[PDB]
Amino acid sequence: ENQILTQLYGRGWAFPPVFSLEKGVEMAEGAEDVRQSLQILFSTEPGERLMRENYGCGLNDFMFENIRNELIAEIESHIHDNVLRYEPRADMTDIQVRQSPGMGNTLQVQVMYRLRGSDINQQIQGV
Amino acid sequence: ENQILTQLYGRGWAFPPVFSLEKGVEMAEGAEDVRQSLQILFSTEPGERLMRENYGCGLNDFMFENIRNELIAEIESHIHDNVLRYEPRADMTDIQVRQSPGMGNTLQVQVMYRLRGSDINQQIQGV
Amino acid sequence: ALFHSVKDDIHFDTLLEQAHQVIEKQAEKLWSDTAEHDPGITFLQGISYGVSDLAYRHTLPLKDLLTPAPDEQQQEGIFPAEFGPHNTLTCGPVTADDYRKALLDLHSSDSLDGTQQDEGDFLFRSVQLVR
Amino acid sequence: MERLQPGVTLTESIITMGQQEIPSAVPVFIGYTVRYPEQSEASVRIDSLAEYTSLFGDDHVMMFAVRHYFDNGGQQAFVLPLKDNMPSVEMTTAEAENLIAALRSATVSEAIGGHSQITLILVPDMARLNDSDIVSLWSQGWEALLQLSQVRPNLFVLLDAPDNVEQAQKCMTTLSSDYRQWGAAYWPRLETTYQKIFQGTVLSPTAAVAAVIQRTDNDAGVWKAPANIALSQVIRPVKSYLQGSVLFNSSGTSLNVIRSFPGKGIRVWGCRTLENTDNTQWRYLQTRRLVSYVTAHLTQLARMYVFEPNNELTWMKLKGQSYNWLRQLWLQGGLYGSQEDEAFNILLGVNETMTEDDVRAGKMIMKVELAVLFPAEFIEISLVFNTQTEALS
Amino acid sequence: IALRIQDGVSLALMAASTASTLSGGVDYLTLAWQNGLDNLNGFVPGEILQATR
């Protein structure tokens, strides 16, 4: 949880925007900005940002369509070229799309990513 | 029946040219000029306009010929490239040519058109 | 026509470039990520569109800004009818010359009664007021 | 302009469009009409609005549902009019019972159950009682409608939900019919672009959904879910979307909502039947319509050799023709299998399904089991970080 | 072009939809000036906007 990765990715506001009485707004630092920069993109849908009209993952335009191998291969293609446009700091390395064992309707996507320029593991969980 | 569609297509004289004591000549406004501009073209035949020699649908040069699938496909071709030359404001979208169930000699053409630049339905019938 | 000259200036793309330059000078060390993802810029992009909304209402033409809502109006238009050029430029009859201008005006149809409102010249063809 | 001499004379009469005849999705509109002039038949087929207005009058609530059905892309429909009087501007409680008692009547149950072409029913006149009706009056109308879809095999019912949110949650809980899987409820009333753009007429939502059920049947078959498709002539749902977020329940009865996406149009959001999920298999609308599509197309194969000798030969001609059709449906992406013995199975033998007395009584017993698919309504992103496994080249 | 508004699309969002068929869309100010908008959000969802170039 060091100061070095802040110099590669910068400090920004945390996506749960919780404000504190000391230190002001909680700042998402370097390795944790790039994870939260992916959490903002998957959580907004395109068109509801104000002037940046096409920003956000459109997974809404293909749901309520049946789970087959052709829908799964359309998610991995869509989720790959969208992180390329709106996330320059995180390179994707694998996408795993599969339907859950418990409930058959829901399917769970898992994005594995590395940060660009750096191969430094996170020590433990936090911020 | 608004003032907005008048700004796209203009006001012109109605094709039944009936004159009134108030408001002068009855004016065909925006969405209704383009329908009546099609009614003028189908109703004149080429050569009887004064100086515009080739203006009007020549459906007269193929009638008294037998109803087959080759006459019907020549009407839909003729009625398509004629609305392109003499109606720039109305785009054709479908032609249905079929002979009537009652009388076998007469055949009835049906031109479906949209106006250019605008997708606004007409609310009810009128003018 | 104030809108056409200020049109490049009251704009989202040019107000946002103003707003990034305040951040890049004053908080470049503590706030170093100004990309399109973070909640800091999306609050600013909400505000810098609201200012572009707010500054557009100033560039409406002055006859339409100065008119009130139709529920509350003083009777005649934008400036009251006492403030027209007929009352703002004209002065009172003090000279013997504009005594003559006023007395020459008086007319039979200006009378409140009599002569079926159609007959009559002006009441005096000439007057002369003097000490 | 000589109309009797031979030539080209333009007319005002509108001739019909070339119909495509989608067989597995065709609605009835059972409602009050103003004219009621048809004296030959019970329920008649309409094709266009200009054919309907000449045939059933003008300026009523059931016309604006037909007018909105033909705008969203539907091409054929039936109209079974109610014979009673057209109601007032608002529905009185003495008159609103006269509609639901006419929905339980056999005068409208025989016209639906006798025609055998209709695959789904709907009332656009149920939203007429949304004002000044008084909660259980809605449930008395739904229990009449879901019972009406039991007269014959392939029937479905699209039905209106009340706009008030407390009234919607009560009518979901206090329904208590044993045929709940044949219905589907779409919540908000649409504000269409028909006069009285300033005050667009408030409209039932089910007339638009029956056209997009017919529209997704044309290209992607019955196995595709009819949600997430744009609606044509609507401005807005008259209720907000955030006010109806308690209508969806993943454990209880869930009601389909119509959402407004910015830049993406007004959309149907949810393909759920009225259902309380205690291990139920007919949870989604597309599962109930697929399994009733393979009953109504296996009866058309099994009707062809009724009155046949019932030997061992005419079972292998039935086990062969139905296996060849279910495989043809499976190879269209319809039945959830990696191999054909995982998708479906049929059995017909004299020691498998039937007894020796059932051959003597003269009956065949066919046992069709079939798997179906799931609609992908929830999507869960996980976002894990993976420089752990880069593994030093 | 004439456009029909639908339920809470903004003027910034609607002027991007003009760029489909207007060879570079009208700016969200110059779209509001041509229609004579009193406000940037001063349109009802039933209203028809006009986008000339």
Image (spheres, coloured by chain):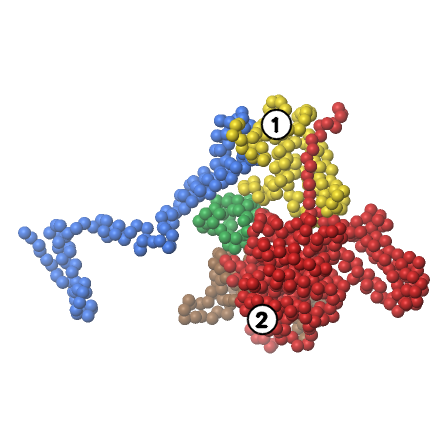
Chain colours: A yellow, B brown, C blue, D red, E green
Give coordinates of residue D196: x percent, y percent: 51, 62
Q: Nearer the viewer, residue D217 or D371?
A: D371
Q: Chain of mark 1?
A: A
Residue topped by disc 2: D86
Residue topped by disc 1: A30
Above or below: residue D300 compared with residue C19: below
Q: Nearer the viewer, residue A110 or B79?
A: A110
Mark 1, mark 2: which one is toward the viewer? 2
Q: Chain of mark 2?
A: D
Is residue C95 toward the left or the right of residue E5 in the image?
A: left
Give coordinates of residue B91: x percent, y percent: 59, 58
Residue sticking out furthest to the left: C131
Is residue D298 toward the left or the right of residue A79 in the image?
A: right
Above or below: residue D87 compared with residue D315: below
Q: In what element is the residue under mark 1?
A: helix
Q: Amino acid at mark 2?
A: Met
Give coordinates of residue B28: x percent, y percent: 49, 64
Residue at point 69%, 31% (across, down): D385
Residue A34 can be seen in this image: yes
Residue at point 62%, 22% (across, down): A2
